[PDB]
Amino acid sequence: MNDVNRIRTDIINVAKTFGAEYSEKVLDEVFQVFGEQFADNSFMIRTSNKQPDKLGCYFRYHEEDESQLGLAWDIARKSGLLSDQGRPVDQLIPEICETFPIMADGVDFDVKHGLAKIWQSIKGVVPVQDAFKLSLPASVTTHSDFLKNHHLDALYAFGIDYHHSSVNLYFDTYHPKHHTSEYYKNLLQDLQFQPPSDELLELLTNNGEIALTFNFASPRIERLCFYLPFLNREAVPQNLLNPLLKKYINEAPALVDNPGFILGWSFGPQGGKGTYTKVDVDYHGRTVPLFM
Ligand SMILES: [Mg+2]
Image (cartoon, rainbow, N blue to C red; front, side):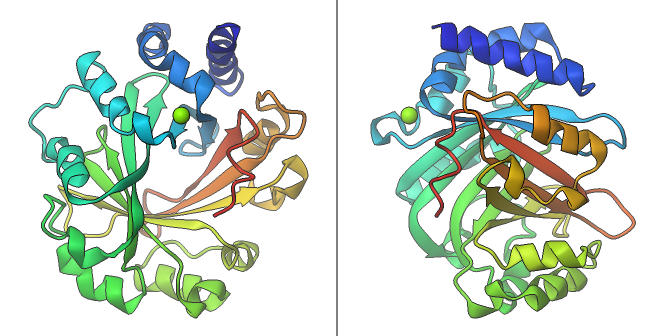
């Protein structure tokens, strides 16, 4: 519809305002194949901090319609947008759908490189050990004691990152320690990841997602990400945003007067790669208000 061409226009406007590498050919191939799903589903536009003065630009959508579960993968495979190169990552979505009942799934795209990531959410939570028979990076099982010790063992979602040959596991925050700043401080210390500010630690006690990143090349836990929702531009803690990300909060395109935002804090090895901020605009205004 008009809604589909409006969405592609907004993405190019973002990528050009905030200096993001993009490719109009790849956007065209994606929108031809997924454009309707972007209009008709929970849809978000992401900006991230990975370079000092150049934001990256991403876009994602989230499918809750039970009769549609699985199509994003089939569509992507048929259209050539996702071509399985025999990689270890390539068999995981088939193994996941056989093994667990799926409640939701999603697709993340990069405005220069295309389909980047597909995620699957489980109906219910499972002991993370139930996933050890999947072809996951060996670093999952070799950290099973760490996972138990830090109460990151109520598993409910998989992110399959095809650009990085990595897997993100999402863990439900079931334990009373998950509502205390000290737990997040100690988790990041135990991982020897970059320490967070005190404002962020206090925010983290709120109800958010937590994901851990495992990769097939590395025996270590590579990354950690906390996602937190915010009702509107006012609710965003702007002390934790560099000027370029603060500008995005104020000018990010949406179809609502006061769109909510989902904020993401990535952490990695201290004095190394992996520590940055992600900012997702709730483009339809219905994604964020559906807290847990
Ligand atoms: Mg839908």
